[PDB]
Image (tube, coloured by chain):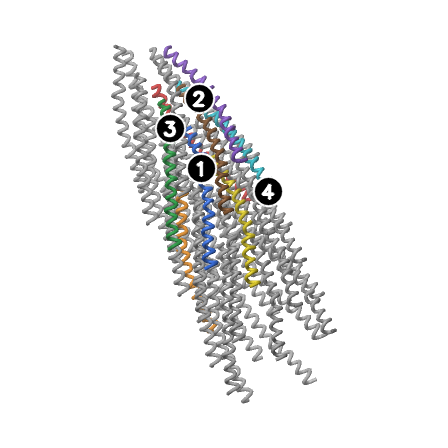
Chain colours: E red, G yellow, K cyan, M brown, N blue, O purple, T green, V orange
Amino acid sequence: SGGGGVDVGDVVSAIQGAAGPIAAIGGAVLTVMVGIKVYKWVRRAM
Amino acid sequence: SGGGGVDVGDVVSAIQGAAGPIAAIGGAVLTVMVGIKVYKWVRRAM
Amino acid sequence: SGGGGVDVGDVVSAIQGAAGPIAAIGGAVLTVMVGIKVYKWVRRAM
Amino acid sequence: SGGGGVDVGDVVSAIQGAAGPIAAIGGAVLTVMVGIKVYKWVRRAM
Amino acid sequence: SGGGGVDVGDVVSAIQGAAGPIAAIGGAVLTVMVGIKVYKWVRRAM
Amino acid sequence: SGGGGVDVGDVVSAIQGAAGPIAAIGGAVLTVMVGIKVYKWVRRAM
Amino acid sequence: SGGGGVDVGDVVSAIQGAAGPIAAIGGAVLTVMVGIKVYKWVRRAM
Amino acid sequence: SGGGGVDVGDVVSAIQGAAGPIAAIGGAVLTVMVGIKVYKWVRRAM
Amino acid sequence: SGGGGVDVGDVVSAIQGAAGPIAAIGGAVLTVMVGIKVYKWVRRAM
Amino acid sequence: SGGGGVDVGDVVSAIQGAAGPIAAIGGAVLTVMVGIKVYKWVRRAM
Amino acid sequence: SGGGGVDVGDVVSAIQGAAGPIAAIGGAVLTVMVGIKVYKWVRRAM
Amino acid sequence: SGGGGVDVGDVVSAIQGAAGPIAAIGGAVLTVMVGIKVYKWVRRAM
Amino acid sequence: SGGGGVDVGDVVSAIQGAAGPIAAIGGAVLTVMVGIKVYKWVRRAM
Amino acid sequence: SGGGGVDVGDVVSAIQGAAGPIAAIGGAVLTVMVGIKVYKWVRRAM
Amino acid sequence: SGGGGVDVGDVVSAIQGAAGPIAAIGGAVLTVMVGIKVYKWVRRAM
Amino acid sequence: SGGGGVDVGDVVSAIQGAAGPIAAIGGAVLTVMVGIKVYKWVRRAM
Amino acid sequence: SGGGGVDVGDVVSAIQGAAGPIAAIGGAVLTVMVGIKVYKWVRRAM
Amino acid sequence: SGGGGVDVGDVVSAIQGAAGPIAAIGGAVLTVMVGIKVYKWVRRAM
Amino acid sequence: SGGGGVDVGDVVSAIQGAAGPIAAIGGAVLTVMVGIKVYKWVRRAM
Amino acid sequence: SGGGGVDVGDVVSAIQGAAGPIAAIGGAVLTVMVGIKVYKWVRRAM
Amino acid sequence: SGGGGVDVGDVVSAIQGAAGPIAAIGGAVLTVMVGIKVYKWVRRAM
Amino acid sequence: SGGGGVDVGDVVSAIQGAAGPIAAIGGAVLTVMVGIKVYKWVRRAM
Amino acid sequence: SGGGGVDVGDVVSAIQGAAGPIAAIGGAVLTVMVGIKVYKWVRRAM
Amino acid sequence: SGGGGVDVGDVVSAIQGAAGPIAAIGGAVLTVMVGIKVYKWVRRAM
Amino acid sequence: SGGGGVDVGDVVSAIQGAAGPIAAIGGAVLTVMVGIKVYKWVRRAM
Amino acid sequence: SGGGGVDVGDVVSAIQGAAGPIAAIGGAVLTVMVGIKVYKWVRRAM
Amino acid sequence: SGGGGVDVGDVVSAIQGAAGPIAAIGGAVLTVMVGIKVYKWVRRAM
Amino acid sequence: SGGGGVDVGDVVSAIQGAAGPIAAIGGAVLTVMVGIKVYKWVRRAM
Amino acid sequence: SGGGGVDVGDVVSAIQGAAGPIAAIGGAVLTVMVGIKVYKWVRRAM
Amino acid sequence: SGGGGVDVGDVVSAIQGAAGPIAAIGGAVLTVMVGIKVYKWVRRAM
Amino acid sequence: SGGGGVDVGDVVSAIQGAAGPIAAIGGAVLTVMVGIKVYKWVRRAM
Amino acid sequence: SGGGGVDVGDVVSAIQGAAGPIAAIGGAVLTVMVGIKVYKWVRRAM
Amino acid sequence: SGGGGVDVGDVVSAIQGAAGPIAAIGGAVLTVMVGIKVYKWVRRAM
Amino acid sequence: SGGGGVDVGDVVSAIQGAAGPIAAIGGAVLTVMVGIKVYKWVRRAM
Amino acid sequence: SGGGGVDVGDVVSAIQGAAGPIAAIGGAVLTVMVGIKVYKWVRRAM
């Protein structure tokens, strides 16, 4: 009950929760990466 | 009967039962982990 | 909270932020690239 | 700051800057190309 | 500096410079072309 | 130097030079053309 | 049942679902890209 | 018989069975991923 | 929802939106290009 | 004879025999695991 | 905003603007070309 | 400014300027052409 | 359906539609071009 | 069967199907492009 | 709408409009050309 | 025999078999992709 | 002799032998994987 | 002498000797394991 | 069928059809041109 | 066999087949184009 | 031998073999493409 | 000696040897791939 | 001395020595792996 | 003194001393192990 | 052999062959054109 | 040797060899094209 | 020494060496490609 | 000292040293790869 | 130093050096091309 | 040396050499063209 | 040799040869033209 | 400090430094490439 | 406190700190890589 | 109470507490690791 | 004091100290590994 259920419950919320901000880096990384290539496609179509 | 059968029975239900929440962390960990890579595949396909 | 939320937050701002200047190279690269072809279209229309 | 902002800044100035002389070839190429055709239009109007 | 500025500089001088003789063909071509028609206008005015 | 200057130089001499004989046809054509009309003016003045 | 079936089900809907907007960028990117070249083909056909 | 055969049997059905939905995420992930690149190939062929 | 839908939405508006000015260069490039050839057709029809 | 030979004989058949189903989980686990990655290689080759 | 709108704006003004002088060559070329033929029509009407 | 305005400016002055002497041939050609026909009109009016 | 059918539909109407005015320049260009030559044929037939 | 055969089947119909409208842009683009040149050939033949 | 319709509209008015003065040269050229031949017909009819 | 030979056999047939439909997407993708460029080559040859 | 030599011998033949079919999945997986990319290279070369 | 030296001697030869075939499983296991990954690297390099 | 056959069919009828009126200008141009020369032949035969 | 041979076969018949009507535009375009010049040669020979 | 030599052998024959029909599309595409331009060269030479 | 030297020796010959046919697919793949583009370059040069 | 020093010495020479052939597989594996990709880069550069 | 101090002293020197060669196997094992993976990283980077 | 030699052979016969009728228009055009001028020379010689 | 030297050798002979017939179309195309213009020059010289 | 230096040495000679014939295809491809366009430039200059 | 410092030192020199020849393959691979594309750019510029 | 500086140095001299003869084809191509048109201008001026 | 220098050398001799006969058509075309006009000038001077 | 020399040779003989009959029209045209004026000179000298 | 800072520092200077000569190939490649096209533009303007 | 907090603190500063120079290689690598392609885009736009 | 409850309590706070800084290294390690790859993705998108 | 404190102290200095050279292999391994890929990125950007 205590250790098993409750603590493991904390594992779920804390782990995937703290991982949310990790996915946030994903969004920010995407802003830049597609950014440099919009530059790449422009130069294609100069 | 008592100590052997009953107590060991408790071992089964309590141990694999408390382990259920452990598997729950597994699900939560999965939400995040695949999350950061959906970010990785996007940047591939920028 | 600390490591997850805050640090990942830094990942977002620092990564896509530092990527901004990367996009800047994109603009500068564009100035030159279209430049050499305005030269190409002139010679077409000599 | 350093790597991202400063270095990328260098990318802009160095890349589109070095490209300037590339556009210079454009001007020089134009002197010749229109030159051979002023010859072409003269022969039209012999 | 080196590759960009200097080499591109060479592009300008070498390209439009080598094109000068191309324009020379223009002058020589003109000597002949108007030549055959001075023949054409004479025959008009026989 | 080689391709540009020398070869183009050849263009000039070869083109306007070979055109010289073209102008020669002009002289020969003139002998005949004025010839038929000296015939035309005689018949005017019969 | 729970973790396997249900959670994985969420993976499908959440992942390919969130990816829909990613494809939306595709449409928007297309508006611009073909746009710059309609400009390129016009200049061909000036 | 009981623990070995039966329980292990459960391992097979439960594990690869619960994994089925995991493969489902695979299908859903595929819908999105190829989606963003149909966008990439269009922009190639603008 | 957040990262997927909202951020990707931003991708669409920001990317094809910033591309609008790219198409603007298209219009401006067209003014010049057709300009030099109106010059070319005049000289045809001298 | 009895305890040593016979009982130990039972150990062999019962232990490695009950272990057979354990290997069965191995097969079932394999169905799923390779399954999720056929998904991974598809997304590589999107 | 910055890179997209502003820089592309510069593309328009700089490109079609620098092209203006290109059209100027058009006017100057026209002065000469019609010039040599006013000579051609005079000789027609000798 | 430099390449566009200045160089194109050179195009105008150099092209229509060098064309001036081309028009000079026009004047010289006219001296001869009308010359041969003053001969033609005399013979009319013998 | 949405992205493919609808957006591409927009491509058709927007692209060939915006191209209509491009053809309009064609008509206007024609007014002028034939105009300068009606001048050319008159001078033929002076 | 399910994921492989059925889902991939959807890939075929959805992808090449959604691509149909892409080809539609092709037809519309063609209406305009040939349009501007019918204008180009007219001006040739003024 | 903007780039396509409006800008192309400008193409029409600006191009055929600027061409009007080109036709003006046509009128002026005609004054002279017929002028020199009224001289030619007089000398016929001396 | 069982797990090794038979199950692995299933791996072969199921994996490369389910992959067949994946190749089917390849054919369908090809119909569209070449489709948009037949449009590209037409506009070249307008 | 018995347990050591003979049984271990069985380990070799049974383990690497049962692994053969595992390599078979390798061949089958290869048929599909290269299959989807022959599709990828075609679309490159559309 | 007897029990100590001789019997222990037997321990050495019998134990590490019977272990030889154990190492044989090692070789056989290696044939398979590297086998499945030659399959993995091929699919990388498809 | 649709895009290829039908649309191209439209190309034929629309293009050579719209060209009919172009030929109409031909007739009208002819009325004037022969007109000015009936004037030229009269003055010959005054 | 299926995807390769059959589908590619479809590529041939569908592509060059749909291109037939494209050539049809060629015939129709020819009717008009030669049409406007029969007008041009008449005015030569007024 | 089996997997390596034989299967890879199949790769060669199946891949470049199925590619043959791909080249067939090449021939068919060529029939059309040169077709539309025989139309282009005719209109040049109207 | 046995397991180490001999077996590993087999690894070398068997692995890079079986890989030879893999390279064979490379040759066959090349026949097709360059094949489809000889088609691409022809259509360029139609 | 005996067991410790001598036997352990044997461990060193026998273990890293037998491992040499393991590295040999490394060389052979490399021949093949780079082989299949020289095929991959050729097809890039077809 | 004798048994305790002296003999135990021997334990230290003999035990950790004889263990030195054991660590020697460690070095030799390391030569091989990193060896096989330098092979693994090469194949990554093929 | 097939695609290259045979198909290209078809190109020759089909292209220059279909061009024969194009030359036929040449003959027919000649009948008319010289026709209108036999009219022109008659009126000269009224 | 085999794949590299021999196969590439085949590339040379097969590619430039199959291209020979492509050049044949060139000759045939030339027969027609000059044909239609011998018609054009005749009508000049009617 | 052996594996590293010698084998890698083989990589250099074998890889860039086998690539030589690849460049040979380049020469052969060039014979054909320029061949078809000498045909293209002739038809320009018919 | 011995095992740690000395042996690890050997790791550095032996590993990055043997890797030098690996980089040598890099140079040789580069000779070929750029080689095939100098062929690609020539055919562009045929 | 070695691979980078020296080998790349070879790239420069070998690539632009081998390209010299490519420019030589340019000169030779020019001899012919202008040749066929000196023929074209003669026929203009017959 | 080989591919670059030698092959390109062949380009020069083969291309401008094969072009010689092209110039031959020029001479032959000239015989006819001036021929039809000697007919034109005779009829002038009837 | 073949295409260049032989085919161009055919150009010469076929073109100037077929032009012979064109000159024949010249003779026939002359019979008539001088014919109508022998009528003109008679009426002068009535 | 040592490994991190110093060695990585070496990475920067050695990598981008050795890359300098790579850019040198860029300059040399440019000399040739523009060279072959100055040949292409000359033949345009023959 | 000591081992946990302090030492781990050192881990953070030392690890990500020493990694800074690793990112420095990133900047230097970028200088070169974009460098070789500015060369690639120039040759595109030659 | 004392030893069990209190001391174990200390185990929890001290162990997971001292582990906090261990996770701190995780954050710092992440700063660097993603750092070197932002460098990797830039070079992809150069 | 002696055994605990002093000896364990030796453990720290000796273990992490001897590990320093282990990290040295890390630096050396890095020189090579990035080396082979600078080769990989060059071939990308050939």
Callout 1–callout 2 Cβ contact below 8 Å: no
Disc assigned to residue T37: 3
The mark lying in front, picked from 2 and 3, is 3
Between disc 2 and disc 4, whose residue precedes?
A: 4
Residue at disc 3, secondary structure: helix
In space, the residues marked 4 and 3 are separated at their CA atoms by 50 Å
In space, the residues marked 2 and 4 are separated at their CA atoms by 52 Å
Amino acid type assigned to the residue bearing label 3 in the image: Lys
Disc assigned to residue K3: 4
Amino acid type assigned to the residue bearing label 4 in the image: Gly
Q: Residue at x 45, y 34 (%)?
A: N36
Same chain shared by disc 2 and disc 4: yes
Q: Which residue is mark 2?
A: K38
Amino acid type assigned to the residue bearing label 2 in the image: Val
In space, the residues marked 1 and 2 are separated at their CA atoms by 41 Å
The mark lying in front, picked from 4 and 1, is 1
Q: Is residue V29 above or below residue O13?
A: below
Q: Is residue V22 above or below residue T25?
A: below
- Pinpoint residue E41: horizontal percent, then vertical percent: 37, 22
Q: Which residue is mark 1?
A: N31
Disc assigned to residue K44: none
